[PDB]
Length: 233
Length: 235
Figure 1 (cartoon, chains in turn red, yellow):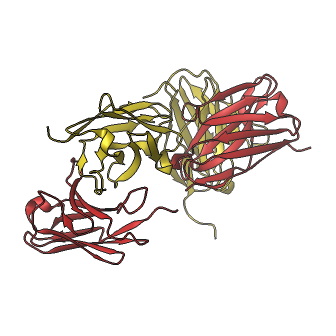
Figure 2: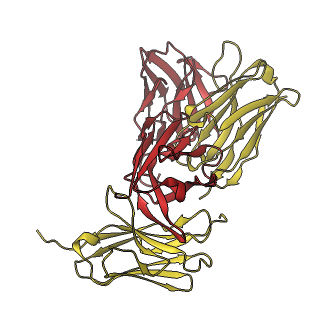
């Protein structure tokens, strides 16, 4: 019989979710060798994550998955397993199952075809437009955000200067936060929200974020960079 | 006192490591509102991470950190905490402490200065430095791919070949032994910690990505890979 490793169980998983992969072997007994799991992020290299020697119950894990991943085996079914908990986007990869040659052979002579795990939507998504805009000092700037669902008027606007923390400008769609200059203003038109700077001042060149607090969790727009007309800046 | 939030605890961490961030609050009582954690990856936007209501310990998280991050509070010290386990390259970001303004005011009116958390990739594992990263070659060319181990790995080195959409295939084992069935145009060699894969005459079926791997210690480590692409045409 031909030596063969067949992985299964991959698919799309929500972040923080969990998944169990299996690797069915034929042509040999997994009891007599180490079974490894090696993964490959899309377009990246190879990373060993775990191995098991079912005869002795030996298991080893890479530091990047220790405490999160569990390797096991069922020799009666000649199948190894990889249990993956609290998955993140950095776990998206093709998960290969492989084996050592046995005896004093420590290269991986046989690999499975691989199974793809993709770690991924009820959150309210906010879409700001444009992504960036150039303006001259004193111009009238208007930035728009669109909520994927109705958020009443529970929308806030924040300004962030490079290297600094965000600072609140507008709350409840149209109320000016105390201390924020008069040239800033907000408005709503259904699911469309607008931030308006009447006459641009040099200290207003920054990135602006919309945010909804109608429901949990709070979600931000991707941001709008407002820079001076010209190149490099 | 003016309202203030001070973060601390960030730093450099290897993948899978742990880190504990602190947010020391002053000018207000954290029992009166929510304390949030918001992070920002370099050059990217703002992502809400977690929140806690220190009055009754209610906590919620973003899905991207569930099961790995734990937010907590010590009302006696007016301080919130973010324990980060199983750290990960996607967690590299500046982490901001923030609060909701209070009852009937759900904006984040006060933010901390932020603390930087960097998840590395310089580690105790043996590094395998492969070169080149890509090579354009014609059929019949002689090709050499070399890899340097960061320390002695004896001859416990293997060379693998991976075609697009396929699994890696073993070519050379123990540094210079040809795997059964692999053509004789493939050969390996060791010079100290330098390991070289040689294809005497490149064939049309040889265009793939090639990986060096050491198995002298655990974990086994792979080189970054060398993509050999075709130069010319046969159509």
